[PDB]
Structure formats: C-alpha cells, structure tokens
Image (cartoon, coloured by chain):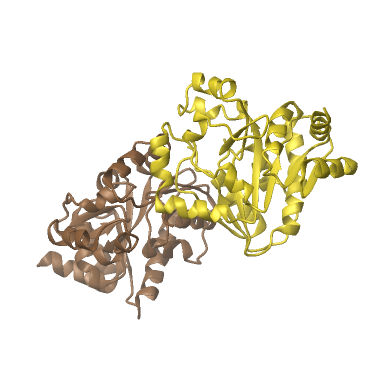
Chain colours: A yellow, B brown
Amino acid sequence: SVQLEQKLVEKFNLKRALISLDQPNTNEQRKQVAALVSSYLNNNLQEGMAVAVGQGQNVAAVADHAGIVTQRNARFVSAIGGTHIINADHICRRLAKKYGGSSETLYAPAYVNDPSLRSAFMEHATIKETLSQARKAEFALVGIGDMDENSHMVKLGFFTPKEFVEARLNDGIVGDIGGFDFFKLDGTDADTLMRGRVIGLEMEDLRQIPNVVAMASESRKALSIMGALRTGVIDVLATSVSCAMALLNLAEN
Amino acid sequence: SVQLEQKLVEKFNLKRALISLDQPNTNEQRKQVAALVSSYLNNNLQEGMAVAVGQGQNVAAVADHAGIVTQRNARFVSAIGGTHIINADHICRRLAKKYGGSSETLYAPAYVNDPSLRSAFMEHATIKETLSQARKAEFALVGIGDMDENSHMVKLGFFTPKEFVEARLNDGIVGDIGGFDFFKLDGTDADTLMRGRVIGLEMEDLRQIPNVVAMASESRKALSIMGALRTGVIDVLATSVSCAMALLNLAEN
C-alpha cells in the first residue's frame, strides 16, 4: 500500500496519496479513508488556517472519525450552500468541534432551479464574502461523487431526470467534486446545465487552493475518480487499495 | 421588582414579566436580563421543543450567560438570515451547545437590497422549510431594538440613509423585533420599505408562537419597548426595573 502511494504520487502529480486497506463494505471503507485524512489534518492544519469543506458522506466521515486530535483555532468554511445529503455546514460545525476551531456558514441554499436565481445569490455581498474566504483557504476537503450520488438534485426537484441523463450523455459528466462542480472523464470542465443549479465554489477555485484533499472509497466509481484526477486540482488523494490499483491500471492503459 | 412583574403582567396581558435590578451600564444590564431568561428557558424548554431565535446583543447575552442548565435535546432555529451584528445562526449554535440540543440554519442572508431579491429567496424550498420550522416553534427569543440598532442595514449598503430616516418619519417605525419586523408606537405594523430588505419571520408569525420572549435593557428605548408591547405578540417580557417603571407610566398616562 505504501508502494502504491509512491506510484500514485508520481503518476498523478500529487503531494500525497493516503491509501487504506480494502474493507468489507462502503461504510467501513469510508471510515478507514477518513481515519487517514483525520490524521493528515491533525498534523497539517495550523491555528489560523482554513479548510473549504464540501458536502456528502466521504467528507462527513472525517468529521465523525473518533481519533485524537490536538486542539487548534482553525476555520472550517462551507464551500457549497445548505440543504433542507449531509450538509457542508453541518460538517464544518462538527469539524470545528473536533479540531477546536470555528465554522463559517455559506448563507445560501446548495441548489436552485434556475441559473438566474443562482446568479442573484452569487452576486450577493454576504454570499460573495464567504465564497472569498473559502477560495482563500489553505485546504479543501472534498469527496469525488458519481452521477448517482448527485441524484438528490433531481429527487429534490431542482433538475429534471431528463436533464440529468442528458448531463451524462450529451455533456459527458462522469463525476462531481465537493458537490459543487462537475467534470468529464478527460478532466475538462464540461459546460453542463447542472452547475447552473448549484451555489458554491468552482473548479478554478480548487485549482488555486494549495491543498485539495479529495476522498473516494468505492472502486466501482473509479471512472469518476480518474476524471477528477485528470482535472489537475487534487493535491492529496485518499482512497482504498483497490481504487489505487484501478487508477494505475487505467493510467498505464 | 416582584410587584412590578404583577402590574406588567396585568397591564400588558403577558404570561410572565422577568425584571432585573438596574445596572451601571447597558452591558451589565443585558447580562442580568439574560440571566433571568436563561433560567426561564432552563425550566420550560422541553426535549423536542424548538426556539425561533432572532439576532443581536440582547439575544446573544442569553447564549453567553454562564449559568447551570440541564441538558435537553431542544432545537434552536434561526428566524432571520445570516450576516457577513451578532448573527441569529451563531446564537443558535451557542444555545445548542449550552442547552445540549441542535441548531437549524436559515440558508439565506439577513438583508437584501431589493424586495424582488427578497421574494426570490423567500419562495425557495430550502428557505421556506426552515421558516416553517421557526413558525411552528414553541418559543421565540427576540430582542426589541430601536431604529439606531438597525442602522447596520444602512452601513452595510442594503438601505439608504434617506430611506432609513423616512421609515421613521413617514412610516412611523419606532422599533424592531428580532431584527426581522418593524412596528409603530401604536403597535400596528407599518408598511415600511425596511422589511422589503429583510429575510426572516414576520409579526404574524410571532403572534401565533405560544411563548414569545422579548428582551430589552435600555430605558432610553422605552418608546420602542412600548410599541412592541402594543403589537400584542409578546408573552414573556424580560427587562430592567427602570424600563418597567417607564412602561407603567406610559400606560397609565
């Protein structure tokens, strides 16, 4: 697994690769991946630094990991709006409690049904200020999701099932990062209608955050993880042995 | 001071009046008023009940009061959006920590520069859900502010100084409750441009919350407190001996 880390770092231009042994199910896998990320943050997140935090189960596992961490006054800033899916805001609050710092809420919903409503929220001074804080963070903590993980935008009524299938088929979206931006298998940003329905950071923000820590546990989602690595924004990849093997195979071939 | 409580209850149709002795300055007064409210909530807020929470220094003092309270699983729900002024969201988080429950964020800013932007946020499913939770709360914890306490809407650029003076002079606004609604000295809701710039609950919501706890410490703000009492929405008034004397004098005369 340490040999795997070196190959991943070399192959994908990472700062680090944190690889957990394969577990019996996805819950257990997320916990073990989250353990390595928790320790990484414990050692690296200094007082006065900030983390831009995305949403969902991979990220939530880091907040829920019950390991020992030193207390420091760090900030946890939502990188995506709230939901009425584990909310980035809730995760930041749990992280602040765990690591001994503070959290900073993005006062806007995660999803809207129209890019004009998106624009209206995004131009608002209160929303812009928090997004600027997240853009200026030293770290980002994000999950890599597959299209099926985003299906809640549809089930919540913000995007049609027809539009959703078309994002995949017409626009070639194979995954999301942090919940807030979407990519193709080749790592390019696809103009997709999807992102017009989300309030949060974008891919270019992640490209300029020094330490983007991205997390995925499921090897069946290796295409999404590959797409995400191809965007070039990831600095620390935390994942399982099988995912690592899959990525190296896909890259070699 | 106990005699004062009985007269206030009778005169203003309250459930309770919590009266603190006069203090040397407003900070100390807010602390002592907040002590009585903290104890009231300790005894009355049951597991599974909720509090709709407004913004500002009077309310924040209750969260910051360092008394002993029993832990119970109550909810603290923001009744007004966030600010980039002590935010209702921050207060709810501190209350949840203190009383041992949870908090529920309103994912929208407190202020907007245009009632059309207000309407767009207010119609959004995520915002409507939280506002419905706050409307259905057993308690509300709100401060009674004077126009000068709201001047931040102006300083933050959401409302012009000219509009602000006109809200007072043309529309007769003498105070706010919770940060989110405004009233005249006679207790009627004034159609004012001000409320078109705020996202949160309104006076009619407070009228149907069973236990509206309203807090003010400054006797120089007695006109605002009088206006607020005249709206009829207040169930528990927490304030100082001098404010109580002022209110009884104003009512008698």
Quadrant of res B136: top left
In the drawing, does residue A48 fall left or right of residue A12? Answer: left
Q: How many numbered marks have been drawn onto this rendered protein structure? A: 0
Q: In which quarter of the image is the N terminus of chain A?
A: top right
In the drawing, does residue B67 fall left or right of residue B34? Answer: right
Residue at 72%, 54% in the rendered image:
A41
Establish if A171 lies above or below A187. Answer: above
**Nearer to us in this view, B179 or A1:** A1
Residue at 88%, 44% in the rendered image:
A2
Determine if residue B174 is in view.
yes
Residue furthest bottom in the image? B24
**Nearer to us in this view, A199 or A12:** A12
**Nearer to us in this view, A213 or B41:** A213
In the drawing, does residue A84 fall left or right of residue A226? Answer: left
Establish if B155 lies above or below B132. Answer: below
Determine if residue B136 is in view.
no
Residue furthest left in the image? B253
Residue B186 image position (x, y, % from top left): 13, 57
Q: In which quarter of the image is the C terminus of chain A?
A: top right
Residue at 55%, 43% in the rendered image:
A202
**Nearer to us in this view, B88 or B215:** B88
Establish if B106 lies above or below A193. Answer: below
Residue A188 image position (x, y, % from top left): 63, 34
Residue B169 image position (x, y, % from top left): 13, 62
Residue A156 image position (x, y, % from top left): 48, 28
Quadrant of res A88: top right
Residue at 60%, 25% in the rendered image:
A172
Establish if A231 lies above or below B153. Answer: above
Residue furthest right in the image? A3
